[PDB]
Image 1 (cartoon, chains in turn purple, brown):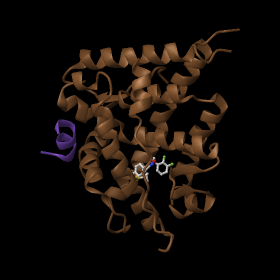
Image 2 (spheres, rainbow over the protein chains, first blue to last red; image 1 turned 180 degrees about the vertical axis):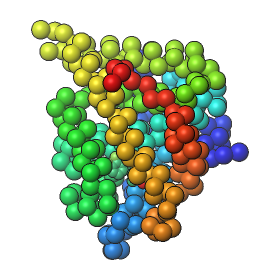
Image 3 (cartoon, chains in turn orange, purple; image 1 turned 90 degrees about the horizontal axis):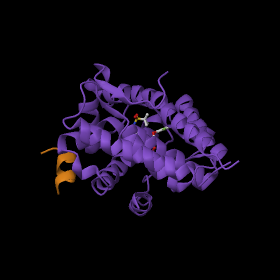
Length: 10
Length: 247
Ligand SMILES: Cc1noc(COc2cccc(F)c2F)c1-c1ccc(CNS(=O)(=O)C2(C)CC2)cc1
């Protein structure tokens, strides 16, 4: 999981 | 009211963490700017999540839009901070990092800095309101798509059209004769003029990223990820900038 993916889904 | 939501979700100001005791070289100023851009990008992602209509777009498209527009959002917010805090006399990156002529020179970015300063001088000329600014920033998040379109093109177009409708209703609050069409076209023109300045900032970005250690310029993790993905797509011509008024 990418940093952008992590922040958008958290 | 979507515009009132925009006003309340506008991210709080962040410090650059600038070390004035260190030599004012291009490598140290650029590294401070990169660190600041990293923090601001985390804020941009948290802002996009709570943006009305943004959650309707699939995850892949949300990522695509953030990655294509990041530079546009950061530079537009810089111009607003510059206009609000210094009446566009200086470039207000953060409260601890305000660029004057000396810093524009030391950063090896003088012509780029002057180009941004011109955009902020347009904010003074137009007397840009916060309401207009917040709508325009959403339009910048939605102004660059892949050449072959998004996964959910119709969902994107519906969101973009609705924020264009919001900007049009907002200009009626600032009339001349009582007309507002003039202001609306001055705003769409100012939006279009962001693509060319951002094309130049990205060219500088990509060069400094390809030669970062040789130039002693540091990049935070958020930027490494954004740039590694965006650099091949932009250089291959896979980005499609959306203009209100074709050149
Ligand atoms: C932070 C931040 N607050 O606004 C901006 C707007 O960008 C500008 C940066 C410098 C001069 C200007 F006139 C700008 F308009 C940034 C920002 C900082 C670093 C990076 C990545 N580094 S980079 O090499 O691409 C470079 C070309 C900006 C320094 C991207 C954005």
